[PDB]
Amino acid sequence: AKVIFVLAMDVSGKIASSVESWSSFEDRKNFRKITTEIGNVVMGRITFEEIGRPLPERLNVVLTRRPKTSNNPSLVFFNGSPADVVKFLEGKGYERVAVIGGKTVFTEFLREKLVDELFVTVEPYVFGKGIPFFDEFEGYFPLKLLEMRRLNERGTLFLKYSVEKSHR
Amino acid sequence: AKVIFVLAMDVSGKIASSVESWSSFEDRKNFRKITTEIGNVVMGRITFEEIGRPLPERLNVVLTRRPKTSNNPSLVFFNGSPADVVKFLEGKGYERVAVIGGKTVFTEFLREKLVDELFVTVEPYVFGKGIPFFDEFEGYFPLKLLEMRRLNERGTLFLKYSVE
């Protein structure tokens, strides 16, 4: 299955901050369509407490170390590596996996080189403080810009990148 | 004068990394055009030492606390704060001031809220390590997108934002 990062950030690369309502209406609308279309969302425990409740109409997979459980079929706490979650999801029939968040989970997938496309929304702000997209990993990923749409008049931008992979 | 930051970055917001030639040909050509039209560039010592020589056809202003002498009329080593620098360039007739870098210089201009427009070039990479745009500071800036432009086929993007 192909792994797709879906995230929103400011111009400086932060995926979260203290600013109020920096996420635009169009960005949220776009996120819902894309993630419900993919059918599942993979997030970290930090991101999951942030959102509060499982995202409707999608299988929510929360990565964590402590064996936890939920009495909601659409919510799953999964103790395992990035490689294992993808495999768990393909066993559910998903051919695409959407990783939506956590500096931690993003870092974990990047380190493991499990990422095929990045769906990035850039909100028109520069946050002096916030949580970075990821920590740090060895190397870098070359990308190719597949699409770019302006979502509203102020300037929220949606960008779709594929990771350039060397092939035969 | 309006203060414009001109920088290139990867998608995670790093302005420097150890990746060879990540700065694209088109990015470099657009940079020259923009800064030469503006007529000046302001940078920190580190960025200047990496650049080595003064950018031709542009008044180069290097921010440094150590009074340094220059024989080059288009090279000025300026000991002063961001506000001083701007007042210095305005005095010379400059309507716009281009700050091109150093995490240090951007951070200082941002703290003093001396910024009106950001000309940002995003290169198609995700750098695992590198130098960030600026060091954490208190506050935020809401922006308005003025223009967006694809510079090449691979996807290098040029974005112009205005500070609300």
Image: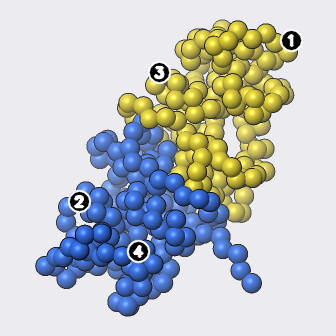
Chain colours: A blue, B yellow
Give whichever of discs 1 and 3 has the lower sequence position.
1
Q: CA distance from mark 4 to mark 3?
A: 44 Å
Amino acid identity at mark 2: Glu
The amino acid at mark 4 is Ser
> Dot 3 surroundings within 10 Å: few (below 14), some, or many (20 or more)?
few
Do labels 3 and 2 touch, CB within 8 Å? no
Marks 4/3 same chain:
no
**Helix or strand or loop: what does disc 4 sit on?**
loop
Disc 4 versus disc 1: distance between alpha carbons?
A: 60 Å
- Which residue: 38% across, 30% down? B138
Res. B100 mark: none
Residue B68 at x, y = what percent? 75, 11
Q: Is residue A67 above or below residue B98?
A: below
Residues under numbered marks 1 and 2 in contact, where contact means CB atoms less than 8 Å apart: no
The residue that mark 1 highlights is B71
Chain where mark 4 sits:
A
Residue drawn at (36%, 49%), measured in percent from left and top?
Answer: A16
Query: Can marks 3 and 2 be said to lie on one chain?
Result: no
Q: Which mark is residue A49?
A: 2
In this image, A99 relative to B97: left or right? left
Question: What residue does disc 4 label?
Answer: A81
